[PDB]
Length: 136
Length: 136
Ligand code: HEC
Ligand code: HEC
Ligand SMILES: [Zn+2]
Ligand SMILES: [Zn+2]
Image 1 (cartoon, chains in turn red, purple):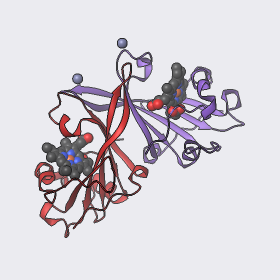
Image 2 (cartoon, each protein chain N blue to C red):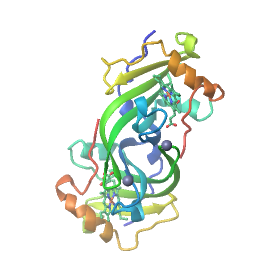
Image 3 (cartoon, each protein chain N blue to C red):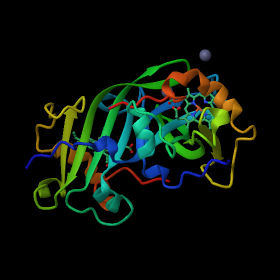
Image 4 (cartoon, rainbow over the protein chains, first blue to last red):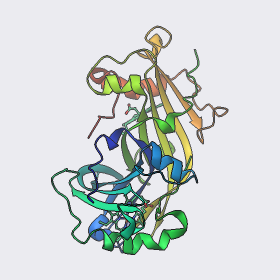
């Protein structure tokens, strides 16, 4: 019933990025530069196939510094993780939701079985609870 | 003596990202959100080895739209490409420097055999002419 830490996610496929700056509704708690990563199984789902069990998506969040009209990546704040298991994570739509503080395997963040996460991702039922779109 | 178009670069290892905002000394031409990618061979150099022939680094530049203090990726503006070949690219320190407008293989940007590119990258001779640092 727990989400596996996604070991080696930094070597996976880079889906997309975004910057969330102060004044953005979501600046607490996902302010910063984020990168979405997808393992091979998650790419099947992102391309418009179905997500196999074992699909993992990672939201990789960095603090940033202002450096002379540049935003420069600072420390990692956290990662968010969605792991596909239709049976084991059926209470949250077939995805397990977990957060790791500073991307550390020992700093698990989710306390409610991922019901809060799922609460928002549920809006994306039609794209199997994934916001991120594959781009060129 | 032309740099090959790095087909498949979007499936490569994501090294790092940076936002260059208007007013940066290099807004013309690299204003936008950029993502650096490395093929397997380029990873060897980023980790502290010698860059082998066939190492390729890509600078993937996107426009962005500031939308309610999110910076949202728009269209690709260009890619920059460094291709390692100690013999063939000897005049520019063993890297071949090319740009592709909108990331299209038909839209070569470099017109001076890469001397201007080399002129700036020479400052990084001690890190084999590479600015980007591999981060976890
Ligand atoms: C709305 C109020 C959200 C809540 C609460 C959570 N997430 Fe979410 N997440 C949200 C958005 C708008 C996005 C897209 C970001 C973008 O750049 O487009 C995401 C994305 C993720 C991802 C990447 C996969 C995807 O769906 O795009 C992961 C892995 C992810 N989120 C995990 C996650 C977890 C673990 C949450 C609870 C701790 C959680 N999210 C909350 C919107 C919202
Ligand atoms: C200084 C005035 C530069 C000139 C002219 C060119 N480049 Fe360069 N480039 C520069 C910096 C500071 C960086 C690092 C960006 C970062 O996020 O840290 C880069 C990066 C690249 C890369 C990625 C590999 C690396 O060295 O980090 C490539 C592939 C690259 N640049 C290509 C490139 C080409 C093709 C150029 C002439 C058209 C060129 N650059 C010019 C600084 C400067
Ligand atoms: Zn200024
Ligand atoms: Zn703003």
